[PDB]
Amino acid sequence: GPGNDPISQLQQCCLTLRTEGKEPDIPLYKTLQTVGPSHARTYTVAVYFKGERIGCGKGPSKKQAKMGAAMDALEKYNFPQM
């Protein structure tokens, strides 16, 4: 349906967040923990930025999980400001 176009691609730039006057940082997305070992194995990942969660998702695979995590950040909007 949506095709092979994970939002992680766009969010990738956000992770670095290149901004003048902003302190340097290097965030990395990696499986946090697995659950449901009894039956189907699931992977849980959470992206952290500036010491705060920016996106988080879950799925039967990292590729699927990461996609959801990136999308979550997108929905929550990066660097929220009214």
Image: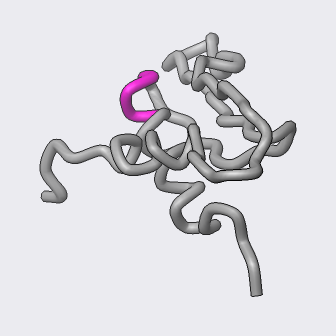
- Identify the main secondary structure in magenta: helix
Which range of residues does the magenta coloring cover?
61-65
Is residue 61 toward the left or the right of residue 18 in the image? left
Q: Nearer the viewer, residue 69 or 77?
A: 77
Image coords of residue 49 (percent x, y) = 74, 40
Q: In which quarter of the image is residue 43?
A: top right
Q: Spot the residue most to the bottom.
A: 82
Quarter of the figure with the N terminus: bottom left
In the rendered view, tell whether residue 66 sits above or below residue 9: above
Determine whether 79 is above or below 39 in the image: below
Which sits in the foreground, 13 or 37? 13
* Residue positioned 58% across, 25% down in the render: 29
Count up the numbered dots: 0
Residue 15 figure quarter:
top right
Residue projecting furthest to the front: 21
Identified at 64% across, 66% down, the residue is: 76
Q: Which residue is drawn at 66% across and 36% down?
A: 47
Instruction: Check residue 67 for magenta coloring.
Output: no
Q: In which quarter of the image is the C terminus?
A: bottom right
> Looking at this rendering, what residue extends furthest in the right direction?
51
6 to the left or right of 43: left
Q: Position of residue 62 (x, y in %)?
A: 45, 23
Q: Can you give x and y, in whole percent of width and height, for residue 6 in the image?
A: 30, 44
Does residue 82 lie above or below 44 as drawn?
below
Q: Nearer the viewer, residue 80 or 5?
A: 80
Indicate the colouring scheme. one colour
Q: Residue at x 56, y 56 (%)?
A: 72
